Amino acid sequence: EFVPPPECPVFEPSWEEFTDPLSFIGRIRPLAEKTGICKIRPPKDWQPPFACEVKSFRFTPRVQRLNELEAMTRVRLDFLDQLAKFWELQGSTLKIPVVERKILDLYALSKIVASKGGFEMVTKEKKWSKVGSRLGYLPGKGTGSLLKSHYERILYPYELFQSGVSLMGVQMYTLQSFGEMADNFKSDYFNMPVHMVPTELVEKEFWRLVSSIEEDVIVEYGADISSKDFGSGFPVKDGRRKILPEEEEYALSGWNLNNMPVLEQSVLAHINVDISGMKVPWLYVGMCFSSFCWHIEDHWSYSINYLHWGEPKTWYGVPSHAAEQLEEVMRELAPELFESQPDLLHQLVTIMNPNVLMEHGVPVYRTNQCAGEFVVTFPRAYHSGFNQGYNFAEAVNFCTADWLPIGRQCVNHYRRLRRHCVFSHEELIFKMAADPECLDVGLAAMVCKELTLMTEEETRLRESVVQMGVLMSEEEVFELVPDDERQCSACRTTCFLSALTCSCNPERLVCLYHPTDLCPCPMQKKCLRYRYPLEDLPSLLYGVKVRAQSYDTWVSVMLEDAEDRKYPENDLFRKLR
Ligand SMILES: CC(C)c1cc(C(=O)N2CC[C@H](n3cc(Br)cn3)C2)[nH]n1
Ligand code: NI
Ligand SMILES: [Zn+2]
Ligand SMILES: [Zn+2]
């Protein structure tokens, strides 16, 4: 019944193309960009050895019930819809909390609390830990009594309202053993050897199972697994190990996902300035039917995903230019609700059958990722998928010159939601501007383009605030204050260039796009806490415009200055030799 979408392009580079990954990825960009995702087959000789011992690799499995795997079911949405309207009536604007790294499933929570007699029943029986169990929350971190606090604050009043009339007060595992599991499950399921069931058939059954209430099917996986803690699946030189000479090659390869963030063309390659969460790969142990939902990368960045070993991983991809279109159809499922909670759209995990997106006009492509192949994801390319079988994968994010203006647009969009920021885009650009040499020429060029656009937009914001009637101008070093303190009262964007403070609160901030929402205290007194006194315009645009317009002229001892300034060498250095 399920209709496979068209396949995304594969790329089989030569050994020479394969030597500089990010340059090879900029070559295929104009083409792969249009499918959102794409597959990459390294030379068949290229076979890095798996660094990890499977027999002693202990991970805690998470679990998936493909029936309740879709969160945007009619019932859950209408519940949140009504619950929001309830809190509007009371004049208090539903605020959905976060528990153990992800949003609280209130619908599930009220269903369960109600199924065992309601809030006070569950309290006077102390079954709040059982609740958090059935909600999948990992014990015994105390979540039981954390839910009670939330239920009471948010759901008990609705429980009463929804209840009778009832309102008067108050208010305001081993990798080894895991393979045994997986292979046994798959064979018992299809009554075949695992390596013998065809891909197309698993694909058909998966999407069946998502919408089937007629039967329940549970599955286990592993994720939220840092290389930092568990170790990378690649060899790397960090003192943990003598690296064998058989491996030396692969420890240095730019396709080793531990080296990608640091390559000369990566944005983070020199900013030893902030833990961005992704300079460090993540591991994904997979099982038949294990799945990941539709998502885009934080700050709309690239993802690259290597399947170390195992059975294939199925993907689905959507080009960036269809991203606004993709979100639009998901929003159709509860427009009123997503009005009040714009970012709730992304917080809510979904596997929308690709067919559905296609019959709504959304381009969708697909591929089977096989052991030893890469998958690349392009900025704002939604993607999802499921595993054909037991396998093991490793992934990073990364950012390139061509991403810088997308990153800037992404903050503008996070700002127009109420979405936190993993880092300050503007800070990133200055940290790059503050080391113009040894900075890939492309970036430099792009930085200038991007930095001038910000000097403008800032000075506009800087001049607009003096009319409003602020006088004093303190000067602060934002990068040295923790993110959570330099965020905006209501944006909530990490401020770096400039923000507004007043004396009502010792430290409660607002970005310059929202200067009214700081505090009723009139603008009469200060304060525009800034970072540079508009004496940056000459300085920093210079160092970059230097290395930007030094390469412009150099092309128009010459082969020496390119070696000193660390220039690139594809067609231009070729003509040298
Ligand atoms: C960690 C950061 C860099 C990341 C991961 C992904 C990603 O999309 N995938 C999908 C396939 C694989 N996978 C995840 C689960 Br859960 C199961 N398989 C990794 N994108 N960025
Ligand atoms: Ni991803
Ligand atoms: Zn004040
Ligand atoms: Zn703001």
Image (tube, grey):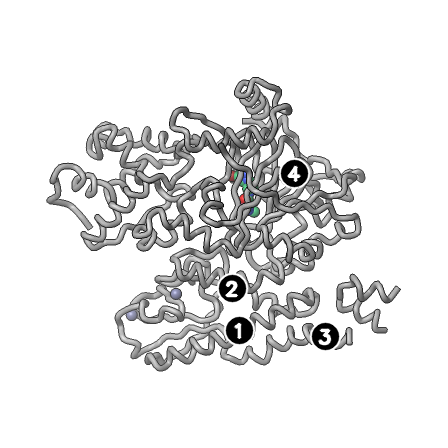
Q: Is residue 195 left or right of residue 427?
A: right
Find disc 1 in the rendering and name its residue. Answer: 453
Tell me if residue 477 comes above or below residue 251 in the rendering.
below
Whether residues under marks 4 and 2 lie with C-beta atoms below 8 angstroms apart, the answer is: no
Numbered disc 1: secondary structure: helix
Q: Residues within 10 Å of mark 3 (few under 14, many from 20)?
A: few
Whether residues under marks 1 and 2 lie with C-beta atoms below 8 angstroms apart, the answer is: yes
Residue 402: x, y in percent? 61, 62
The amino acid beneath tag 1 is Leu
Earlier sequence position, callout 3 versus callout 2: 2
Find disc 3 in the rendering and name its residue. Answer: 552
Q: Quadrant of the rendered structure where residue 439 is?
A: bottom right
Q: CA distance from mark 4 to mark 2?
A: 33 Å
* Residue occupying the point 66% across, 33% down: 309
Quick check: can you spot residue 454? yes
Q: CA distance from mark 1 to mark 2?
A: 10 Å
Q: Nearer the viewer, residue 448 or 126?
A: 448
Tell me if residue 120 comes above or below residue 556 in the rendering.
above
Q: Quadrant of the rendered structure where residue 489 is?
A: bottom left
Earlier sequence position, callout 1 versus callout 3: 1
Label ID, residue 107: none
Find disc 4 in the rendering and name its residue. Answer: 233
Label ID, residue 408: 2
The amino acid beneath tag 3 is Asp
Earlier sequence position, callout 3 versus callout 4: 4
Q: Is residue 287 left or right of residue 211?
A: right
* Residue occupying the point 75% across, 66% down: 567
Earlier sequence position, callout 1 versus callout 2: 2
The amino acid beneath tag 4 is Gly
